[PDB]
Image (cartoon, coloured by chain):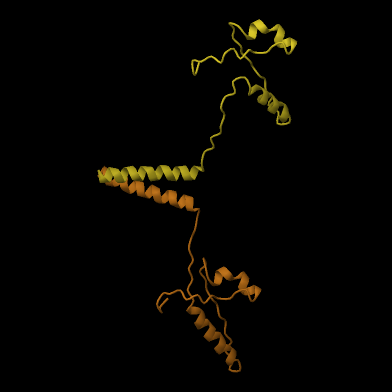
Chain colours: A orange, B yellow
Amino acid sequence: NKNKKKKKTDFILYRDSVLTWLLRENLGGNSRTAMVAALSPADINYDETLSTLRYADRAKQIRCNAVINEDPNNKLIRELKDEVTRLRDLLYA
Amino acid sequence: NKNKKKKKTDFILYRDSVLTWLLRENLGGNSRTAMVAALSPADINYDETLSTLRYADRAKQIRCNAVINEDPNNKLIRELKDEVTRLRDLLYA
């Protein structure tokens, strides 16, 4: 996002566990999402709370790219309909 | 009819079967012929109809072919693109 834009090919590995494998799309792809981190306030539970905080903060840095898709034929037909409408408005004026 | 050069007499041969022998005056000479072939519409009776069409295909076989049309969405896209091209021309001109 910020470095240059080269699309360094470091790929994420999701085939390790079934949990990551089945949540392939939600973690990244055509989905938008939220993380809900619960916390225990007891002083004895300090390290686990810090781990939860740090990984929630890391999860904040993640970008989602949800996009709506339909039949490309219908989308192209609608775009061409808008184009001919624009041209008709141009010549009618 | 095509080349003006009658093919000699191609002496037709009827003395081969009694049916064509008795009807020699009607097929040949100054005469006209017409044939009608019946066809049944059952999907079950396929090869009967196939044989009937095959044997009816003789006697001045007529050139046959198929057509096949295209995906309706593609035709609509092509028509829209042609209209857009005309209008762009309606704009250029």
Residue B71, image x and y in percent? 51, 43
Q: Residue B61 lies in what quarter of the image?
A: top right
Expressed as whole percent of the image width and height from the top left, the position of residue A66 reads: 49, 66
Viewport quadrant of the C terminus of chain B = top left
Q: Is residue A3 left or right of residue B15?
A: left
On screen, residue A22 above or below B3: below
* Above or below, comparing residue B83 to residue B37 in the picture: below
Name which residue lies at 43% across and 48% down: A77
Could you say where residue A90 lies in the image, as x and y percent from the top left?
27, 47
Q: Nearer the viewer, residue B83 or A93?
A: B83
User: Of all residues shown, which one is farthest toward the bottom?
Assistant: A44
Residue located at (47% from left, 50% from top):
A74
Q: Nearer the viewer, residue A79 or A54?
A: A79
Residue at image coords 48%, 63%: A67
Q: Is residue B46 above or below residue A34?
A: above
Q: Quadrant of residue A15?
A: bottom right
Find residue A79 and report its horizontal and vertical position in percent. Answer: 40, 51
